[PDB]
Length: 44
Length: 84
Image 1 (cartoon, rainbow over the protein chains, first blue to last red):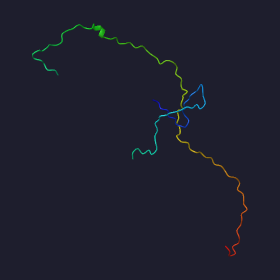
Image 2 (cartoon, chains in turn brown, blue):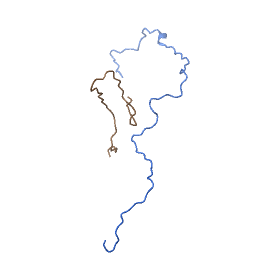
Image 3 (cartoon, rainbow over the protein chains, first blue to last red):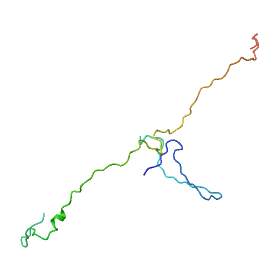
Image 4 (cartoon, each protein chain N blue to C red):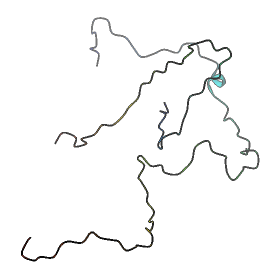
């Protein structure tokens, strides 16, 4: 409904506070997003 | 747009029992005066900044100077006595 749109680099973060951390513990992120590309001509 | 049956016609509606006529009439609901309560604060400590941002970063510069320029001991050429 309200997409996260940072506008300078470093504007919104995602936080996880763990309680127990083992060896080789990681955090696997997965995003979906909208973006605009280059060659903005729009079917010339 | 029905067609009248001439062999078996019918008449208009006859009176039937009714639904107690005042109980189909509503009251007009009587609004009292109201108030958006409290004294509102003038400003809010917003979680996002209200100004523009920049998409790309541009390299900035500032001018510097060099230093006091000295002389030099050049290696000097030979004399052009028709060999050169």
